[PDB]
Amino acid sequence: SDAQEILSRLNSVLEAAWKTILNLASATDAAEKAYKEGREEDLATYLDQAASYQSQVDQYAVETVRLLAELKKVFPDEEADRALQIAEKLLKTVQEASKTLDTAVAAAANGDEETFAKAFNQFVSLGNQADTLFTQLQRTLTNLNKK
Amino acid sequence: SDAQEILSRLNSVLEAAWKTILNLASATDAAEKAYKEGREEDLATYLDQAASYQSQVDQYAVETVRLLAELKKVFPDEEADRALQIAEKLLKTVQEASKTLDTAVAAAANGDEETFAKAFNQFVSLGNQADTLFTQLQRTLTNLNKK
Amino acid sequence: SDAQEILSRLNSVLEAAWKTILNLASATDAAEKAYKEGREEDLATYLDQAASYQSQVDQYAVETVRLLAELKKVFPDEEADRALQIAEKLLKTVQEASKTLDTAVAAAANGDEETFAKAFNQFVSLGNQADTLFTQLQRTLTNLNKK
Image (cartoon, rainbow over all chains, first blue to last red; front, side, top):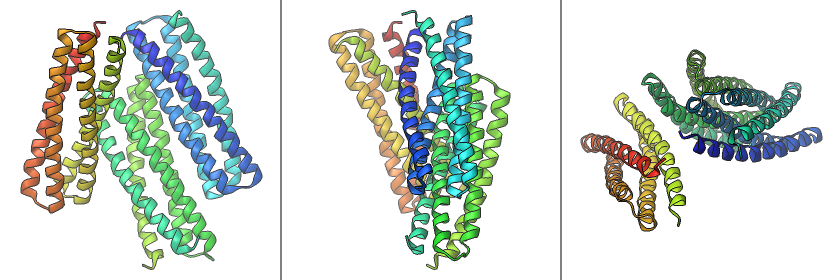
């Protein structure tokens, strides 16, 4: 409650989430390299790291929706509803990435490399889509904090 | 990686997975209660806890598949193939539980109770299917262990 | 140092402690269920989980007492002293709960249902006393926060 704690907690969440997204991208790049190189044990380690980071991204995206949902109850205006709709789409995308990574992780564990490569590429694309939404949300929040 | 060594590592993973499953069940029961009692914010915390334990169960289920896939490489076939098939099904089921719990967590944050309830009930049912597979897997492994 | 950093730290602590109190309630519910259903290994796990959350509650209560005393020094306030005396009752209560839970853990370990049942019932009751004090504490901090 009180929009100013909410907006400040939001900025902290998004700052932590961006770091997690960067770290996830380093794990993703490492996994792709290990796959190309044929190093299956390395790939397993990098996928497990990626899965861990993705779980944190998902958690932060959940918290982001919850904070903006609260903001919208406190100050029901067009802006608040727009910011919440972006965050809800961000959450949908990151959870779609999580599902796709799960498919890829299972396929690599099973040794089904065609399923793995397809799902892993879908996972990379969804991350890039999530990044676009993340930036959009940041721009909207700039308008809501008003310096 | 001898066969006796792999089988030992498996028994330890499944021991740890069972404890996580007990934690997941307590979190699930608590969420159901908070849901029934209309404690929105309490439910949110219990869903986050369930989601964390679920991700831990999924990681153990991945590790279990990886270990059995390795066991099938040290074998010229055995009841390894059957254990691996069960484990792969267990992983698929627990990942479906993660996917449905994600949907529920998002619907709860979005304030969409119909979508929450449908997904949460799917999550619970997949947990029961996973429990059956986990018990089946333990029974299969006992026959591979030789004491 | 500076009444506002102390207040924001107290805000963070009590928010973290409320989550821990939820986790304690879920473990307690789970132990009760395992006890009623006669699943002694499940019960032993859930008592251990309860004890862990209880001790985390204890630590947050310690930290809250220390922080309120610090606030009383640089922002003397009859609400800060009110909060401190509630926080100190809370600490005494949650410690008492830890003691009775220990008695229950030991009773379960010894397989002594008559000691166990008395200790467990006292533990649940103390947890309720603590929940009430925590509510009062929350309201008092809301007063101090003075919007």
